[PDB]
Length: 192
Length: 138
Length: 108
Length: 109
Ligand SMILES: [Ca+2]
Ligand SMILES: [Mg+2]
Image 1 (cartoon, rainbow over the protein chains, first blue to last red):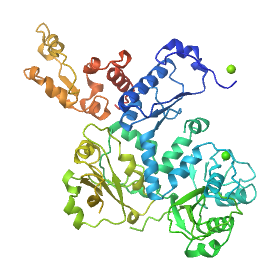
Image 2: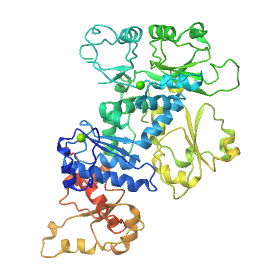
Image 3: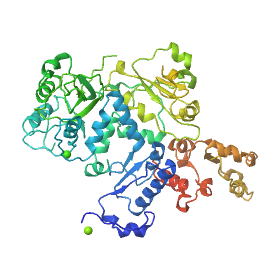
Image 4: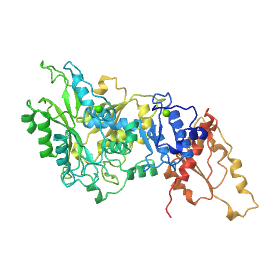
């Protein structure tokens, strides 16, 4: 009841019309990260993007790019708009950024990776390292518009109130834009 | 990332500004225009928007965290650090054999994400920290 | 001479010559490298590129103190380094060492 | 690239030089591409005037700004990779990419 499949090529406009792409909320393109020739796969994804933008230019595209120089080609497409949500997740760029962040602080790559991954709540009877690790990993990063009761306070105050009362930990907010761990001088507002 | 990139469109730019270090769209526009990075003369305006929170790790073995780290709970240390140093602890970088009674020579540590308030803390633990910045340290 | 980006949240310096920052066996021997970052590249003439700019870009974020920056050294076979150097000649504190990362003498 | 085939660009410039047009109506010719292919085919293009060669890639915006593409009389796009690429839909790689790149270009006047 959640997944349907259809046979067709992205380069064919009729197949794109069959799946009612004009009413689709987004289009997701997956890449073969283990191809023998990365350039060929990057180019094939480039023309998949070209075809889907040719059919519907306003559709949202979330696609993987194996290389940064091939990623820069997408920025030259007239329909490729970052404001709309055209997200070219660059595997090489993000992996190198994670490696550099691990260089700044070891063990941060796994901390970031486990946040994006949806994990259940698993317990282990015996006291091992895996028990504590699985307890930690079960936490994911979510986003929510905050309540109006908090308005009129500072971000650290709301952090303490959420951690002590609601058992919730805040890392970033929006100021009336994304602000990561804003200082005590910033004040929360309505619709945060 | 895809699912996380779909259910919240700002996740990718948050990752790029927390990992790459503030990849503003002006820089992306410049890169797309030039296909590379070129030199330029200094501008005094580049010294006011650099005050952010840096990510790093800090040790509980010494310093003012030792007293609360000698058998204390995670919640008390987190609350005290948040109150005092504008800290934000989102995980513990704990040695694999730290919880074991037998003292080993192992050094590598694992990550526990978002430990509870009543979580028992070990003095030899490392925690992940978000700090401020000062512009006159050079 | 560009030490901050247009927004002003990054570190950078003037371009340098290819041989200006390359350290040989002896040049690495006298020059003491401590508190730095080692990066071991494997590849050959037919190997593909990587895009190492994003590996060094966040290390240059300006929300860190300048004295907290880290030297960067790369170790690999000189063919691949000279192949990709066209995109890495504009960054400072970048050393290139020909050879193989499997050699113990190079790592010493 | 180095393995790409030749084109025979003489007939591209030959009719522009027809003498039934006024001399002041002639047009400068600039080519943009990777210097390997240009030095490969230059043996048949060293005898013509008003012919500029620019190393690089046509997908680069800076190169097109240097050429002053917005001021040109006409821009044409040719790919020698139309033969080495096996997949039919992929032989129009660079032509389509560069066409969309120039179409999406923004210019200030
Ligand atoms: Ca969970
Ligand atoms: Mg159904």
